[PDB]
Amino acid sequence: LLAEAAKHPDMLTSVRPNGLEDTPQFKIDIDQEKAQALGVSINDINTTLG
Amino acid sequence: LLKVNQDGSRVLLRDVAKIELGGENYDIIAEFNGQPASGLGIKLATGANA
Amino acid sequence: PVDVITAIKAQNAQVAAGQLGGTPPVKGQQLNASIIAQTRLTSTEEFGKI
Image (cartoon, rainbow over all chains, first blue to last red):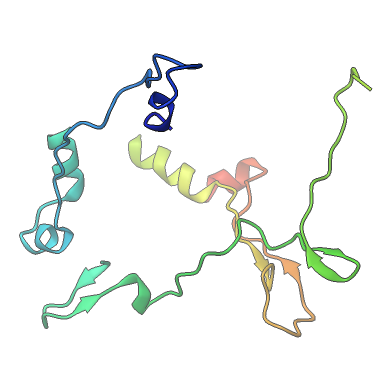
């Protein structure tokens, strides 16, 4: 929509979003099996992290 | 994952229970002309707004 | 006193225990009745023998 709306500058202008665009994020995959194997509590993990 | 056997085995949720996209409650079944259907019963706030 | 408290919260409670063949049922069920488990206590004597 934002691309097609910039091709009609004769009856429409300044077509833009108001929010924000996608940003990089950091995913931490908590392997559950290894967490149980090593004998750590998942609650401990999430609590420490947060 | 539910538990890990010292054998080295693995006990998944699918191995003890059916996983199924169901409903919250199964008490309510609606039929239009016999044919299975759903619907919306609309009440009226005390203070119509006719 | 903690042991007493917990013993009260354990032996004097009202638990939800579903129904005998509630919804959903297998096809052809002819019996549907609610199930009673632990109910509240009602007298001095009842708390007496906790």
